[PDB]
Every structure is written in C-alpha cells, then in structure tokens.
Image (cartoon, rainbow, N blue to C red):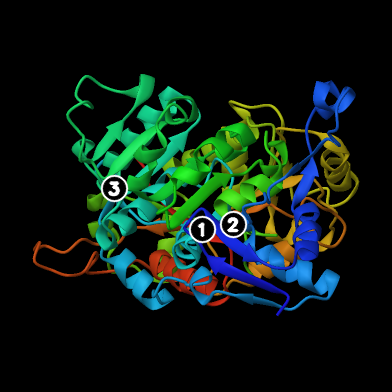
C-alpha cells in the first residue's frame, strides 16, 4: 500500500511511506500556533506559524493514529496499520460489571456504587487503553480515576502516574482514593509540594501523584516505570508540558486525560488527542435527568407501618409533617442556586402544606392549581421570562394541560407515582413542546420504610417492603430497561 503504520512504542507509532506522502501527512497533522505573531522566527524568520506533530523521524504521537483513516479517504491512499496498534483489552462488559459488583467502594462509612456515566467512562477507557474522558467536574472523576487505577493494579506490573493541577488537589486525590477504600496511603506516593513527611519512604508505591510542574522536572528514564497515566483537568496542560514527557512514557499502555472544558485548553485539541487518544463523552443514553432519592425512615416507624394497605400507607406518608419539611428544604436549597423548581403534588391539603413551609422561609414561591388560567399563565410567564429561584408548587393536572414552562430546571415528585413511569413521558413531552433547556432533572422520591431483618445472617437488606418502596424499585428497574439517565441517592429523613 501507500502507507504503512508500524508499532513503535506506547507514545508513538512509526510511519513508512513515499517522501511525497510524508509531506502531505506532515501538513495534515499540524495547526496554527497560539501567539505566533509575537514569535521573532515568524516576524523576521522562516516560520509560517504552524506546529507540526510529525517530524522527519516519522514518529506520530500514538493517539492520532485513528486519524490516518481520514487522511487516506481525503487523499485517496490505502494504508496498512499494525494490528497491535488497535489491540483492545480482553474485557467483556459482563466481566467488567462482575468485577465492579465485587468491589466494596465507600464514602465515609457508607457503601456506594458508581453512577452509569462513571462506569461507562471506566469501561471505555479500559477497553480502548487511551482516551480523553469528557466529563464535568461533578460526576466525580475522582472515583473514575481510582477505578481505572485499581483495575491496572490488579492486572499489570507497572506503576500508575496521576497528574493534577495544584498541590491541594494532589492531596485531595490521595485522600479520596483511600476514602473509597480502594487504596491505602502507603500505596500512594505524593510528590512535589503535596508530599507528606512520609512520602519519601514510598519508593515502591504503585501510584504516584503530582503536578505538571513537578513531573516535568523528572528525567526521561523515570517515566519508564509507568504503565498507566492520567491527567485530571487536562485542559490546563500546555503543549510544552505534554511534549516534554510524551517520549518518556514509552511503556504507558494506558493513558487518560479527563476534562469537561476541552474548549478552554492551553494546548491544541490535536496535541491532546495525540497524547491521550480520542474523545469519549459518556453523556449518552436513549434531555431528562432522573434522581432517585431513597428517603429512609426510623426503624421504629418501619415496624409500625408493616401491615398497612397501600391506600393507608399513602395517607400516612403524605401527611407526615417531617416529609413535607424535607421536601420544602429540597425545594428551597434548589432555588437558592438561582434555579427554578416544580413541586408536584396530588392532594391540595398536601400541596398547601408544602407551600406554607416554603413561604415561611422563602418568598419566591407560588401555589398553582386554582385560578386555573389568568394567574396561572401569569406565573408561567414570570418563569418563561427569566426569573431565577422560583419554586412553583403545582398539581400534576396544572402542568400537564396548560403548557409552556421554559426555565424549568427541577421537577420534584412529592407524590410518588406507582410502578409506571408515564409521568416522565409527560414531563418530557411538556418541556419539549413549547420550552427549551430540556436538561431538567426529575427528583423521584422513594419512601424507604422497609423492615430490616432480625438476624444479621440474613442475605436480604429488608425482610418486608412498604408499598412506596416496591414501587420505587419497580420504577428503577424500568429506568434501567428504558436506558434512562438515572442516579440513586440515599438520605435519612431524620
């Protein structure tokens, strides 16, 4: 063929082609330098101001290899690519989930599980070896890094290098790693200013954490020990820095750059892709963001409720003053972020109860179900305009019929549905009819009043389920099947 791409090492692939093909490629893999007008080589020399990532030694940063395909389709060339360049991990999604399920991950003393977008990021990173994980600062990348690092540790012999922006984050990263209980401080060597008085003894630690400023001062050889490398908030990484260590990471089979601000990067996207591989945004589904909140009740309340019919249980829970207070608080909290929330209720005694708690602590609150139109669209317009921190307490009826609702950021289901999720279709519909933002999050409250087993030798979490819990679980299973964007959280009512 015209072009042959051979496996060199884990930092670069090597190209063999005609000298003519070489120069076309050399211009392909280039971009306009930032501030090139201030460079004297440009103003008085022979520089055109572009930077070329493909030098005469014919070595191309590993992560840009997938772009060769595009080069050929654009210049009508045929190329052969060494299969070991596209080698993937022998890891099925089933084994991954199995591995994940057997892990005891914590947050303080509470056992927890990774959100879907976190698992998909880890899985994608792992299977493809090198990738830029495009995720916001929320969505805890901390755990994502810990899982990637954990996997490596259990399957390979090299060390894992993690680069963060500041020394404070150096510490935060380490502390989080132990918090999850996936690593111990003895396994994590902090370098540079983030080091503790005992990091000097940790020469064999499988995990090294530091800043670009420190890492860049290390000798080429030092980099041979890492099999995996990660850079959190990699958009703060400069091309100079990347180019400085790129060649030392020759055995670094796994590389990840994590960021949710790729558009504010010091370096050019091309430079990032060459070092970390292509971009993967987990935010993928098949609009609505669902938050399943497990509201746990006092064990004693749990024991008294047992035996009550569905109709009775709804009466009891819905009328509970503390639950009304909890919801009000959730609403307020959400509004204080200059965001608008919708508190859905069914029975007026409930709605007003909730409305009065809020009002006795927050002004921008509106009750809606009466004066059906004139005052209804009035509010619906106060929101559509651009008001912020507006909590509106309405009934499922109101918001279904007369629609518009633009700036709607949150919808709090104060009256749990049944085992069906149609309400979501409705919310989804109404929002994607007259208004936009459509990235509203729905808070699905599940009232967990399940009864714990007497013995500790019971392999069940609960021995008895109240109805609202069964329903919430039915709803969760439905979100999974329908592959919705959902997350689960637990909170004690008291």
Q: CA distance from mark 3 to mark 2?
A: 34 Å
How many numbered tags mark residues here? Answer: 3
Please tell me which residue is depicted at 47% across the width and 30% down the height of the picture: 216
Q: Which residue is mark 2?
A: 63
Which sits in the foreground, 221 or 341?
A: 221
Mark 3 or mark 1, whichever is nearer to me: 1
State the residue in front, 101 or 436.
101
Q: Is disc 1 placed on a helix, strand or loop? A: strand
Which quadrant does the C terminus fall into? Answer: top left
Q: Are marks 2 and 1 in contact (CB under 8 Å)?
A: yes
- For label 2, the crowd category at 10 Å Cα-Cα, with few meaning under 14, some 14 to 19 and many 20 or more, is many
Looking at the rendered image, the disc whose residue lies closer to the viewer, 2 or 1, is 2
Q: Is residue 477 above or below residue 117?
A: below
Q: Which residue is mark 1?
A: 130
Lower sequence index among marks 3 and 1: 3
- Which residue in the protein does label 3 denote? 106
Q: Is residue 22 above or below residue 46?
A: below
- Determine if residue 401 is in view: yes
Mark-to-mark CA distance, 3 and 1 = 27 Å
The mark nearer the N terminus, 2 or 1, is: 2
The quarter of the displayed image where residue 64 is located? bottom right
Q: 10 Å neighbourhood of mark 1: few (<14), some, or many (≥20)?
A: many
Q: Position of residue 340 (x, y in %)?
A: 70, 40
Q: Observer-nearest residue: 207 or 158? A: 158
Q: Secondary structure at mark 2?
A: helix
Q: Residue at x 21, y 25 (%)?
A: 200
State which tag comes first along the sequence, 3 or 2: 2
Q: Could you tell whether 105 is left or right of 252 in the image?
A: left
> Mark 2 to mark 1: distance in Å?
7 Å
Q: Residue at x 53, y 71 (%)?
A: 86
């Amino acid at each position: 063929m015209d072009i042959k791409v051979h496996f060199h090492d884990f930092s670069h692939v090597r190209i063999d082609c005609e000298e003519s093909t070489f120069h076309e490629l050399r211009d392909f893999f280039s971009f306009e330098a930032d501030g090139y007008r201030f460079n004297p080589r440009f103003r008085y020399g022979n520089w055109d101001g572009r930077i070329r990532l493909l030098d005469y030694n014919r070595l191309l940063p590993f992560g840009l290899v997938g772009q060769i395909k595009k080069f050929c389709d654009n210049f009508g060339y045929k190329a052969w690519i060494d299969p070991q360049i596209n080698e993937k991990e022998e890891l099925s999604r089933k084994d991954f989930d199995e591995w994940l399920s057997k892990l005891e991950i914590y947050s303080g003393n509470k056992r927890i599980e990774p959100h879907w977008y976190q698992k998909d990021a880890v899985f994608e990173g792992l299977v493809n070896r090198r990738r830029i994980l495009n995720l916001p600062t929320s969505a805890g990348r901390s755990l994502i890094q810990a899982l990637l690092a954990r996997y490596y540790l259990e399957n390979y012999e090299g060390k894992i290098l993690i680069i963060v922006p500041t020394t404070a984050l150096t510490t935060q990263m380490a502390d989080d790693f132990v918090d999850y209980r996936l690593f111990s401080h003895a396994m994590i060597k902090k370098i540079g200013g983030g080091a503790s008085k005992d990091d000097k003894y940790k020469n064999d630690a499988p995990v090294v954490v530091g800043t670009w400023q420190t890492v860049v001062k290390q000798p080429k050889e030092w980099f041979s020990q890492f099999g995996m490398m990660m850079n959190d908030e990699c958009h703060l990484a400069t091309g100079k820095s990347i180019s400085s260590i790129i060649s030392g990471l020759n055995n670094c089979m796994f590389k990840f750059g994590l960021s949710g601000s790729l558009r504010d990067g010091k370096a050019n996207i091309m430079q990032y892709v060459g070092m970390f591989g292509e971009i993967f945004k987990p935010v993928t589904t098949s609009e609505l963001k669902i938050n399943s909140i497990f509201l746990r009740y006092p064990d004693e309340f749990t024991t008294k409720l047992k035996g009550k019919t569905y109709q009775e249980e709804i009466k009891i829970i819905t009328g509970l003053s503390k639950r009304n207070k909890w919801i009000a608080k959730l609403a307020i909290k959400l509004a204080q972020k200059d965001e608008n929330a919708f508190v859905m209720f069914k029975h007026v005694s409930h709605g007003k109860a909730i409305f009065d708690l809020i009002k006795n602590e927050y002004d921008k609150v509106y009750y809606v179900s009466g004066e059906v139109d004139t005052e209804t669209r009035n509010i619906m317009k106060t929101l559509a305009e651009n008001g912020k921190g507006i909590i509106i307490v309405a009934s499922y009826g109101v918001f279904s019929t007369g629609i518009s609702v633009k700036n709607l950021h949150h919808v709090v289901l104060a009256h749990g549905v049944k085992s069906k999720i149609i309400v979501l279709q409705t919310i989804g519909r109404v929002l994607r009819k007259h208004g936009s933002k459509t990235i509203a999050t729905v808070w699905d409250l599940i009232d967990d009043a399940g009864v714990k087993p007497k013995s500790a030798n019971t392999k069940k979490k609960y021995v008895h389920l109240n109805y609202l819990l069964k329903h919430g679980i039915d709803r969760i299973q439905r979100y999974a099947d329908e592959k919705f964007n959902y997350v689960m959280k637990t909170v004690n009512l008291l």
